[PDB]
Length: 175
Length: 51
Picture 1 (cartoon, rainbow over the protein chains, first blue to last red):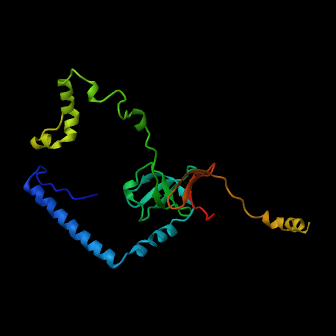
Picture 2 (tube, chains in turn blue, purple; picture 1 turned 90 degrees about the vertical axis):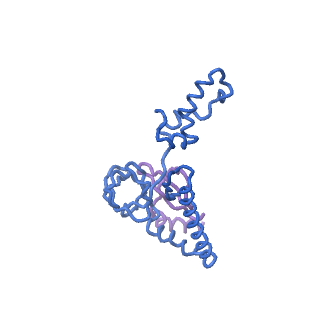
């Protein structure tokens, strides 16, 4: 969850261990302090009512537009469904990691300021090409190759299983 | 008969209230909101009453 990179040798070593023990120990101090605060005060009421202020800012008839160009500076050009093109202000509670051109953005009714985004379909082509599990059989049904299967395993499977091997020596897998 | 006449006599104000749009629900979502297509306009994220 957006944790730090150890960037020690990255291979089992004493420095990878100490940078790792340190992050663990900081997480431990943080967890202890958080648990202490939660016991001392739930803050459930305070965390709540922020949802209420947000929902107050975003009125009930939220409008699904279609972002079309982010000026890179908490502004946007959002197109309403008919086809008109407005130049609205991006507010502070929208997760900007989810804002890219073409995303179905959720605008205010009276002010069209961007106040959220929505998910989209996962099947541009993902479903039609992905094959899932092969109905035929697993590696059991294949025999006689032995060497060829070994080649493929090293080419495509081994670089996923244990990257350390390739990484240790500085060579990338075959293409 | 009295009720019928009273209803007819009120019906003039009841018939001056606005209407309500007909929308096709896309998918209920979130706390209590829904995503509704309002033909011909675009989609919305509307609230849902208590009932």
